[PDB]
Image (tube, coloured by chain):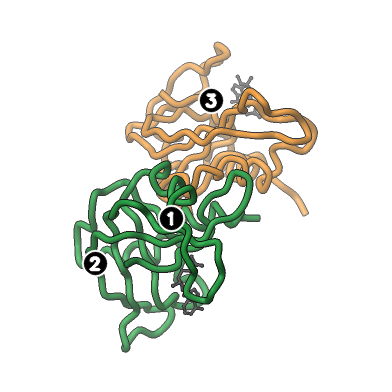
Chain colours: A orange, B green
Amino acid sequence: MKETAAAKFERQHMDSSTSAASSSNYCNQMMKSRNLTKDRCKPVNTFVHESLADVQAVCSQKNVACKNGQTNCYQSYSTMSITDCRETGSSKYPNCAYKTTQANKHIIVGCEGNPYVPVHFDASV
Amino acid sequence: KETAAAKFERQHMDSSTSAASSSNYCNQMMKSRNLTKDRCKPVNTFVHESLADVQAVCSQKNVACKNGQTNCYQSYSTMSITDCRETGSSKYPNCAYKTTQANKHIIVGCEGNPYVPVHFDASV
Ligand SMILES: Nc1ncnc2c1ncn2[C@@H]1O[C@H](COP(=O)(O)O)[C@@H](O)[C@H]1O
Ligand SMILES: Nc1ncnc2c1ncn2[C@@H]1O[C@H](COP(=O)(O)O)[C@@H](O)[C@H]1O
C-alpha cells in the first residue's frame, strides 16, 4: 500500500466522526490509534472535528505565512472545532500520556497537489 | 481501543447543555454519539452535569446494581438527565427515540484506577 502526504494529514489531524473530543481520554486513545507515539511521544498534536470537505476548502482561502517563515500556508475563514493533545508532566515514553483540551479557532494549513489539499498542520489561531 | 471509562463518557455525558433543548435530542444524539452504529441501542441516559460531578458518584452511596453486582453507586444529589427510549416502530438504521427530561439520582457502576463510572445502571 501507499500513503500520500494528504492521507498522512488526515490520519494525523482529522476526526470528522465527532463534533468534539468524546471523552477526557480522547487524546490518549487517538495519539495511539493514529500511530503518533511509535518512537517517541509527540508533545502536541491538534485534531480537527470538521468535515473533510470543509478542511480541504481552506486551501482556497486566506494565504498567510507559516510559523517557520515560509509563505505557503492558508488560514481558514471559519472558526473550527479542534482538540489539542498535550503531554502531561508525567508522560514518559513508551507510556505516553496526554491531556485533552477543546477549542474553537481558525486553522492554518499548508497545501499541495491536484486536488489542492492540506498536507501540513501549521497552527490554530 | 476505547477504555470502559471513555465509553461511559461518550455514551452518557453531555455537559454542553443544562437540559435537552428539543424533543429530537435523542434521535440526534443517539446517532452522533455512535450508539446506533450497528444496531439501535434500546435505552440510554445522558447526564447534563460536569464530568467531575459524575465521577464523584463513585465515592458516594454504595448500592446494588440491577443484576445484583455490588459495584454500583447512587448520587447523593439529583442530577439533570435525559432518558432516551427506542420506539416500537424503530427499525435500524432509521433508529427512533422518545426523549424524556428528568432530574433524578443516578446509579452507576464503577471500576478502575482511578475508580470511575464505566456503566450506567439506573435513575431513581
Ligand atoms: N508546507 C509545509 N509542509 C511540510 N512542513 C512544513 C510546511 N511548512 C512548514 N513546515 C514545517 O514542517 C514541520 C512540521 O512537520 P510535519 O507537519 O510533520 O510536516 C514544522 O517545523 C513546520 O514549520
Ligand atoms: N443490547 C442491549 N439491549 C438492551 N439494553 C441494553 C443493551 N445494551 C445495554 N443496554 C442497557 O443500556 C444501559 C446502559 O448500559 P451501559 O452501556 O453498560 O452503560 C443499561 O440500562 C442497559 O440495560
Left-right relation of B74 to B22: right
Residue A43 locus on image (x, y percent): 64, 26
- The answer to whether residue B74 is left or right of residue B103 is right
Name the chain letter of the residue that bears numbered label 1.
Answer: B
Q: Amino acid at mark 3?
A: Asp
Q: Is mark 3 within 8 Å of ligand 1?
A: yes
Q: Is mark 2 within 8 Å of ligand 2?
A: no
Crowding near pointer 1: few (<14 within 10 Å), some, many (20+)? Answer: few
Numbered tag placed on residue B61 in the rendering: 1
Which x, y percent locates residue B10?
Answer: 47, 55
* Horizontal side, residue B81 vs residue A41: left or right: left
Is residue A15 or residue A44 the one in the foreground?
Answer: A44
Cα gap from disc 2 to disc 1, whole angstroms: 33 Å
Is label 1 or label 3 in front?
Answer: 1
Q: Tell which of B79 and A23 is nearer to you.
A: B79
Q: Which mark is residue A122?
A: 3
Secondary element at image label 2? loop
Judging by the rendered image, the residue that carries numbered circle 2 is: B24
Q: Earlier in the sequence, mark 2 or mark 1?
A: 2
